[PDB]
Length: 524
Image (cartoon, rainbow, N blue to C red; front, side):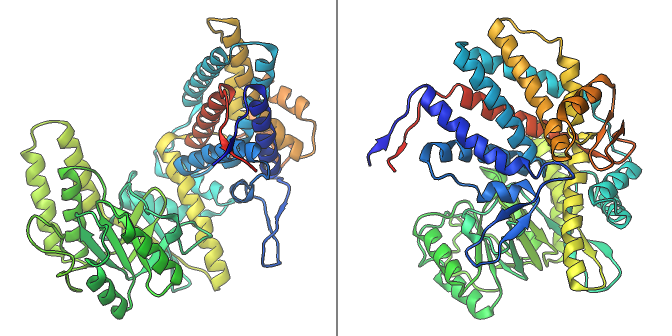
């Protein structure tokens, strides 16, 4: 296992080249007038896309060192995208700008740690100013406006998002399904979602969405860790002869069992998904029992006496539809007795009335809200199936954007919020010259994305950036109409969470990369 080691400036230069390649591939798509990029496929028909997430996913460098740098930048950008629902290309552009400026500063002879601390101070102040500039959208009218704007100025999508948001609640869960009719409708069904995802990425069967979807799947509920397969041969073969998919909810699935599941999924004879149980300790067991009473099944506990071998088909829980993502799952319209759910929620209410501490009180309140609020599913309608799928994807994107907005408000989009906060912080200073240099690096990097957008528009980035900086408030430059004005009023905005998350992960990866000292990677 011989490995190649690069020390000092060599590794940093290789990382700079890798991140430069990744950001040059991704940033061309930034902005409303984003350049097309061609991703060649093995089949023979290349796919032309204008979204940075796919370009980042396809990018992988031949050189090991540059590949490592691009991979870490892509990882932090994907973290930002998953946390916020958008902002891969913005985070990548910010990261590239900070890396370039910080590596130039390091080559001058300044302390990388002081530069990193200055960058962190600058981005913390920028986040504070951005939060100050955020415009809340708690009211339903602004929710509808944000939903409409996010869905490329479509009023029906915004109306659907607003109605569902009001129906389930501000923190509720909303799922999108294709409707059988032309008219679109929404309804509230029993279900819940939790903060656990799929154990193996190979379980995905919908590469376009990057999520696992099952139609009327059985649900297995066992708190015992599964490592042997012989314990689950009977239930697995019962599910197979039934023909329905299986969802495995357990404390942890690993060892030969996980390998058996993944190879069976690859062979496609039986579709099965394994999901780690939510929480830990007795709270995990309580959540598992809540899922069991929601889906009509029963948990399998080694302490009580029932075993996986003796578990039968009717013992497994049943749901109408489940969705598994990398971070969170979802159960939609899980079939279960109404009386059982009412009894369980009454028991949880009794427990919260008898709750002693405040932490367990909040935990029980969150659990009861999850159990009783349910999931609101929206059925999108269209004339044809192609329009149906397009509108479903558009509605999902609008839903993500609106959830981010209602979580953290909205700020002027098009990359002018970063310009505003940079102009505000122009007078910020640190406790050392190197920290001041890092702060200036961060401010210029925050200026960069608007420059990239306007360059994609073909105009001069410097003049437009200076004109935007001269203004105040939500005043900015629109890329589509090639003219200035208030970005919020004229329909260009993004949720504050997206910008904040992109800036924060860009700063974090920049701090990690600037202070990177050496590398360890395998020989070519």
